[PDB]
Length: 306
Length: 306
Ligand SMILES: *[C@H](O)[C@H](C[C@@H]1CCNC1=O)NC(=O)[C@H](CC(C)(C)C)NC(=O)[C@@H](NC(=O)OCc1ccccc1)[C@@H](C)OC(C)(C)C
Ligand SMILES: *[C@H](O)[C@H](C[C@@H]1CCNC1=O)NC(=O)[C@H](CC(C)(C)C)NC(=O)[C@@H](NC(=O)OCc1ccccc1)[C@@H](C)OC(C)(C)C
Image 1: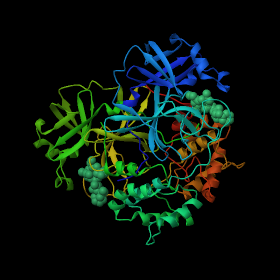
Image 2: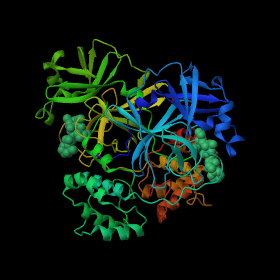
Image 3: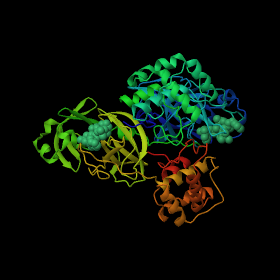
Image 4: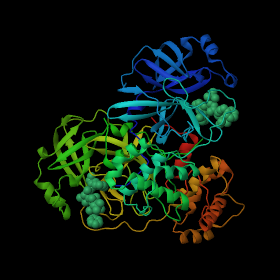
């Protein structure tokens, strides 16, 4: 038993992580087969970052402007081509460590793991989520750009994120691997604000089942509510409305525990209307929304990967 | 900026993780050079687990009783020898992926990362700490035994933990890599209880500096206390006494911020005597003790590894 914020093993992504240097700019890039994906503001300067027209800047460049480096060994670039906000550098060697992989575009609510890098050398791995406001509460310093988020389903790596920029409230933003930003942010230095966040309700309920599975049960009650009446108190507390499709995915968990989904909504209801009054759930003094219903199953029934 | 519970990249440990099967018992084992380290109750049965005399059980065994398996390929055992609570299986091949490594025995307070495995296939990676009561608040299911905790200092892996058993309050216990249990627990199924936990004070203060570095500052104050007078309120709240050696390691952080260590003790003091009254620090409604003063430096000044 026990329940920790857990991350996918990062071995397979470490094998693709390289250093990309251009001008006076060094960031990280992802090397799959014979292609190296990095963010395109690697071609910018400090003065460029104010309102670049990346199509112009890029057309001046030649191949030899791109110092790519895997470990110490220098990759030879032989092509480039900008797709949305990522650059695609065709080099002269395919990555021997290329794993099974795909590119995906996640929805808000879905979670993933992040391997933070600087100069191509991994530094850490955390697990976080795609906020309702298309931001992520991450941990990034200068040079952290080009690091990726990802899920692993047995042998296959689903890349879903690349890092580009920090917003002034300390939150972060970036794109899928096809270059398209999540949310309405642009890779340039002009003011822009995240937009009010909400609480991912379906993930809170998934987490509350994880609390039940692990012996925590003080928050339960006899009460039951109908979803119409839950969603009017959840709004008030600025939670995502709950769809019948949420209740569907929560069924399995509802039956490993014999607690009706509609009863667990009645407990959360009381938790919001009274708070938590000195106690913790799963060692957290807060309701926790960064665990998906399929996250809970993972950790509580022990799925592995290879 | 930003601040997440972060884990070392697990690539190098994944490369050593193998399956060890004996009798009707399957657990995970660690293969470095030509030696495979697993926990010894892999030789037990269900009835044995009540009061085994591992020296007897082991002397009946032959080499061919140990089904070792790295991926699908069957390692050939050619020797064994029990050192404290770990078995050491000499096989006929050295691990091509053996990294630079060492074995260490951590103190309470120090943290490490955990790569949870089942049947040899990694499942997740989390970061946690060696509680003051020689337990760890981990997340483990059946078959999780033989998984390790570890730190990485540039290129070198310091193994400090192997998994053996869960305690009935949901907490966990295990050994260093030389077989010796942390704390007073034994690998057998007879009753034993963790002992009251405390709060690792030096790590709370390290974390509070991380809060300062990242813009959170509502808990600060003009006040200052002398350490004699701090330690009498910290006791009350069942915190570790603070040594002058703590203040020493906290200096660097004290000066990236111009906050005297002795002033930060005066803020924590008020936080315990009043609680936190609706607000969060670093997105946690709690004071967080699983970040070391050298953890904070890592993440807030971006050290990498290879
Ligand atoms: C690339 O590795 C780098 C990583 C960031 C450094 C620290 N954390 C990071 O996420 N990204 C950038 O430096 C990026 C550069 C581009 C804008 C993508 C070209 N810049 C930022 O992240 C800035 N954010 C920003 O300027 O957004 C627009 C804006 C401007 C003014 C007011 C509000 C919003 C960061 C560095 O600026 C702060 C938001 C931290 C002030
Ligand atoms: C090996 O992989 C396995 C992993 C555990 C299964 C789930 N989580 C784990 O940590 N470890 C064991 O099964 C271990 C077997 C030995 C005792 C090491 C031989 N057993 C336990 O962890 C039990 N704990 C236990 O029996 O401790 C002594 C005890 C006995 C009675 C009352 C209190 C303490 C677990 C399985 O038993 C519970 C504590 C969960 C009831």
